[PDB]
Image (cartoon, coloured by chain):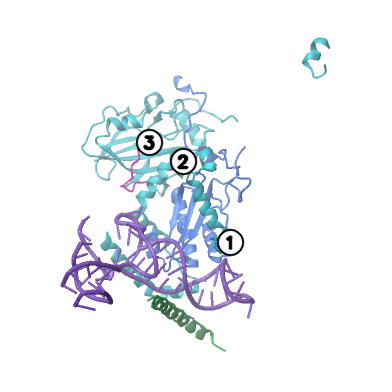
Amino acid sequence: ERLEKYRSFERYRRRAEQEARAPHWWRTYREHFVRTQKLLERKHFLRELRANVEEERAARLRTASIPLEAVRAEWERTCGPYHKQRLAEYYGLYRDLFHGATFVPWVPLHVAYAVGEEDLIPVYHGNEVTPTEASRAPEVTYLWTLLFINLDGHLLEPDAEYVHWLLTNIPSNRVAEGQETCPYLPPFPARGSGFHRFAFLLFKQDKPINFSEDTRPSPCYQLAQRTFRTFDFYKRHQEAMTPAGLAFFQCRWDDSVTHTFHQLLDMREPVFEFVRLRYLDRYRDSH
Amino acid sequence: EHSPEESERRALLLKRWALFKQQEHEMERDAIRS
Amino acid sequence: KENEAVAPEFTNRNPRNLELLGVARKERGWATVWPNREFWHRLRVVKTQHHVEAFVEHLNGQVVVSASTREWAIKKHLYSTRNVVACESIGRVLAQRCLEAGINFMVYQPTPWEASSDSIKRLQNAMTESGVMLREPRRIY
RNA sequence: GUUAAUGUAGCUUAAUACAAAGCAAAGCACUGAAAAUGCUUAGAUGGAUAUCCCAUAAACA
């Protein structure tokens, strides 16, 4: 009785997993392989909800339901930005884009790809959107600077990346007024490279700055001029640029990708795949 | 034999009776501690 | 055409490139311990005394999707944090957060008593209807 | 009144940030008892700084 006994196996498993996370003298797997007033007002509503007999009746009748849409909007306002950072960091955007610099987003950036005019394809964090679905520029809803990247879409150099379209001196929310430094190009992910992560970055602009260096010919179909580095570009403008918004999706190869490489990029489709007696008696076993 | 309506009515107050006892025990346990 | 030049090998850097493709390595160790580690993501469901929480954790130990009833948005519309419906709601909320995160596949390993729980079963029913798969794809060798 | 305690919910310096948290405790079902398990129940800043403090309760009194 003196020894403590967890009343469920998982509690020991969770405790053991938590114990394994911390380093220990004994060998473990990881070592080898590794405001207030608002709340008071909120609480008053909670007591009212508990008091409501109808809610209690549903609970005992196990028929109660909750509206997902209402919860979703509230969640974004309260702690949504913090979760936004986790997804970006988990996908390695910060390490690849800013060389390890980490920023908590503050602007709830949202992007969706317009399917003609009837509907527009969402762009979640870590979303999956086919290149066929990216033939057009997406709608962004959130001065400012708006930038598009294919983090791993570069075909020749690992560190380098290409811009889809870059807008500068964006006034407030409207994006039509931004300078079209880079014309829009549809995604061109190489076949057999799996999922390419594309990150959409929003930077706060303290003062309007003309990015004549970042201006590119419209239309431009050359990869040699599309290649760029986010880190040095951000460093050159780090004084007036503080990132606050994010949105990124993953895309596979698709039939449109063949069209993009050939019709306008005008180059071969890139294809890759990960690759996993006397004299002779002495030579042979017999001797 | 209780009717289904009676069980529903009793079920609601049985929760209150459980609540009334539960509150008493907390006070009773604290009362013993004092 | 000069553009036709293409490099011999790609330089994909996405952490989930292999994982989403299915070629990423799955933990094949821990042969002396139960259960299996052949899962990229796992659903961790923790029921506290007053709150019910469900998390999705990758092999690296970083939760990507975290659903908790203590969160303000869900609870204000949720009558009692501890309830069978709460497990259903958190499952749908966890699914919606799973929808938010872009993760479609996860491995769930309920315990004998947890599996028997109707609330967890309904929570799984909420997950399956929302599309979140309780079984992950097999690794590609 | 002098000394002194002592004031988020049984416990916690959980927290003042994105939640007033986790843990203890509770009804019923399940019949050796217990425990386990399913489904369910109730709650706090009696209080401030960004130490006094009033309340409370003691030795002095």
- Disc assigned to residue A169: none
Residue found at the very far bottom of the displayed protein:
B1
Q: Could you say which chain is coloured purple in the image?
A: D
* Nearer-the-camera pick, C6 or D53: D53
From mark 3 to mark 2, how far is it between C-alphas?
21 Å
Q: Is residue A99 left or right of residue D45?
A: right
Q: Is residue C43 visible?
A: no
**What x and y, as percent, mark residue A126?**
44, 44
Classify residue A146 by image quadrant.
top left
Q: Nearer the viewer, mark 3 or mark 2?
A: 3
Q: Which residue is mark 1?
A: C115
Residue C26 inside the magenta-drawn segment: no
Q: Which chain is cyan?
A: A
Q: Nearer the viewer, residue A29 or A264?
A: A29
User: Separation of disc 2 and disc 1 at Cα?
Assistant: 34 Å
First along the sequence among labels 3 and 2: 3
Check disc 2 and give the amino acid type: Gln
Q: Is residue C45 visible?
A: yes
User: Image quadrant for the C terminus of chain A?
Assistant: top right
Q: Residue at x 43, y 29 (%)?
A: A264
